[PDB]
Length: 460
Ligand SMILES: C1C[C@@H](c2nc(C3CC3)no2)CN1
Image 1 (tube, helix red, strand yellow):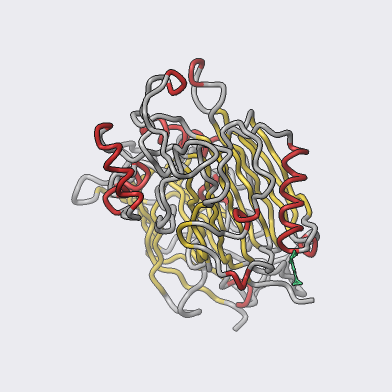
Image 2: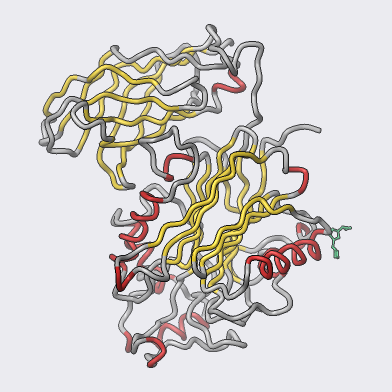
């Protein structure tokens, strides 16, 4: 039975509006409704992994697991195994996988983050799951961010608290937050970003939705505009939105958007918005292809419609050689040549690098770089040809070219990371000096760049 080099992943997000679901929710898992939808000819083909995020979920874990498993069994005739379930208040994440994957999945983590202080602590935050699928790390975040059209900045703050404080993946990757810990990271939920148009334009917006003319609405979507201005979700992807706004509907129909201000809304308007979203971030040059992104039309218990997204995701096998794991493979090496970091910091400390990768027995600390001034104000940290030669555990190019090197640049004075990035070993050539580049971030915000050349030796 061969190990896969691709799997498909279903991501669902649904704000259930504190109501039980209807008796049939299969359209959700089949990616049927509006937007980029899945071909009828695939309906019986199970996804490898289903990740369900709910918000305002009134069900017990048991109640929801029974509905989910019975739904998937009805669609696929497969009895899925529960990988993980984690709930914070009424925010929940469930991960189900095909039974054949049970001994491919390991290192299962769960965590949550509560966002806000005093007033603003008590119902918003995130839950997450991570695990290994053979040689591939997968992370999943379901977040319910702050509501309200005039709180986009609070949403952006919620995002930065969640990526700082959600403790998933390999705790040895200590300089790295979740945005660097996984081959593939999926972040979804009721992100609560709104279409920022005047209240008076509510009926105009509704008209546009009935005409399926989303362009003038998406140009005002706060998540798209905040992302374009690098305020949030830096280096994440989202598939083009081709489905109607998923909020705020009258319940038991989808024929009416309920946007007017009410006591129940705190006298806020809820103009039709794409609150419910799926984004991802994968390591450079790993296969990830969105194959569906849309909303259901027939699930009407909530004032939100469910959103689905499906992905092809590249995966690698758990590699064993005669040598590694448990020793180095003298036939392999990674050399970083003529490298320099460009940092936005005003601080004058010395800096050193750390190289972290599951292709190394443990992380490698460099010597300090040489600080110079850039022509436009910047700190440039030069490493020359002084960087430690990295000794991978396996030299086989079928393994090594699929790996990645995480880089942290740290202050000698404080040992704190000023920037984190990732370099793919999927090179155009081995034994050849080739340009490398990564942006550097810290707390998910841009702090600089790392660039130079790499020379990779494999056993071929
Ligand atoms: C309910 C179970 C659904 C299902 N059929 C299959 C295979 C074609 C035999 N896999 O799932 C069909 N109707």
